[PDB]
Image: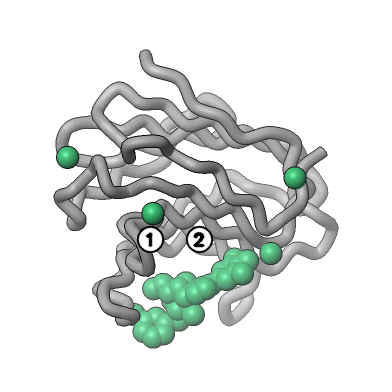
Amino acid sequence: MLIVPYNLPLPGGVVPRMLITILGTVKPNANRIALDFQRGNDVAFHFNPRFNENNRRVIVCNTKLDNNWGREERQSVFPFESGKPFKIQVLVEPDHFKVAVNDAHLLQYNHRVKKLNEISKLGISGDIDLTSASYTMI
Ligand SMILES: OC[C@H]1O[C@@H](Sc2cccc(Cl)c2)[C@H](O)[C@@H](n2cc(-c3cc(F)c(F)c(F)c3)nn2)[C@H]1O
Ligand SMILES: [Cl-]
Ligand SMILES: [Cl-]
Ligand SMILES: [Cl-]
Ligand SMILES: [Cl-]
């Protein structure tokens, strides 16, 4: 379906009520996936499933400013499975990105990058077959 890494333009950046939906399948023996909501070279929101970080599965979220990664936000819930189809929904709310996987809420990430309308690309990378990536306003 789509070539990874895939770039989805976000025209005029993001705004509350914007919903991004990603459909794909995790490859066998996946190691990593990443979503990168980019403001130029900066990464406003990096969402990064790691399948084998010291034999644990964890989602790492962070922001990259002037080429430097900030303080990571980790929680324990890991809804992805090697080999299986998934849906990721990222809903922009006024104070955070809200993420649900497979229709179940996963996590929130508070806005560190304040200029939402300059967050103008979403990169999708890692160990998936990517079916589709799109957005709508709810
Ligand atoms: O905090 C989050 C960051 O963690 C560092 S490690 C680190 C080093 C120094 C300081 C800090 Cl705070 C962290 C990683 O190197 C970063 N990273 C992952 C990817 C990547 C690329 C791909 F192509 C993928 F497919 C993929 F899934 C992921 N690109 N950059 C990022 O995850
Ligand atoms: Cl493509
Ligand atoms: Cl951008
Ligand atoms: Cl804005
Ligand atoms: Cl990739």
At x 31% / y 33%, what residue is drawn? 92
Q: Is residue 64 above or below residue 10?
A: below
Dot 2 crowding, Cα within 10 Å, few <14, some 14–19, many 20+: some
In the image, 8 versus 71, the foreground residue is: 8
Question: Residue 48: percent from the left, percent from the top?
Answer: 50, 61
Asked whether mark 2 and ligand 1 are closer than 8 Å, the reply comes as yes
Q: Residue 70 location, x and y as percent?
A: 26, 74
- In the image, the residue with mark 1 has its CB under 8 Å from the nearest atom of ligand 1: yes
Is 100 situated left or right of 32 in this image? Answer: left
For this view, does 126 lie left or right of residue 38? right
Q: Give the quadrant of ligand 3.
A: bottom left
Measured along the vertical axis of the image, is residue 132 above or below residue 138?
A: below
Label annotation for residue 48: 2
Mark 1, other Cα within 10 Å: few <14 / some 14–19 / many ≥20: many
Most foreground residue, 105 or 99: 99
> Residue 121 in the image: x percent, y percent?
45, 48
For disc 1, the marked residue is 61
Q: Residue at x 70, y 49 (%)?
A: 81
How was the colour assigned to the protein in this rendering? one colour
In the picture provided, is 20 more to the left or to the right than 113?
right
Quarter of the image that includes the N terminus: top right
